[PDB]
Each structure stands twice: as structure tokens, then as C-alpha cells.
Length: 98
Image 1: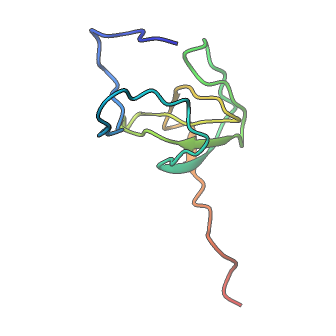
Image 2 (image 1 turned 180 degrees about the horizontal axis):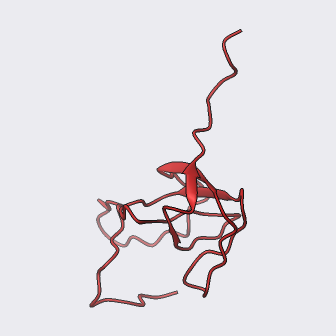
């Protein structure tokens, strides 16, 4: 909804904004993540701050600024989860050579 924390800047995003003027655009339908990973173990968000997902859930890493914790999405749901509870899917682009 709004800015929750201001003083503490532990985690920082990786998005660069070069727009001049009134930048008021509704959430864009198209998003460009950084990578795609899969849940290794059913993760249960202790609170609304974390992301609640199961083993083999669709998680698209968008910001991995933290080598310990990563951020992904699931069915239009964004949260926070450790980079240790996911394994790079490495989705291959194209069928095997044959």
C-alpha cells in the first residue's frame, strides 16, 4: 500500500527510473524478471511479509540483490523468501538435438 520502512534500508531494489514528470502508471501487465526457480521445500510465510508456497511452486526471481534472500512471484503474489529454499529451474529453451 504505502512506504512501510524509511530509516532502515536493509534491502534495496534494482530498478532504474528515468521518467521525467508525473510518473503515475497502474501496475503493468508485463513484467521482466531476472530468473526462474523452483521451491525445494514447502515454505510457509510466518506472516504477510513472507511468501507462502509449496514444493514445486512457480517462483520467478525478480530481485536477487541479497545473496541470502530472493524475491519471486506466484500467481500474482509477491513476497520474500530465502535463496536457499529454491533451485534454479534452468528451463531449457528448445527440444533436445534430434
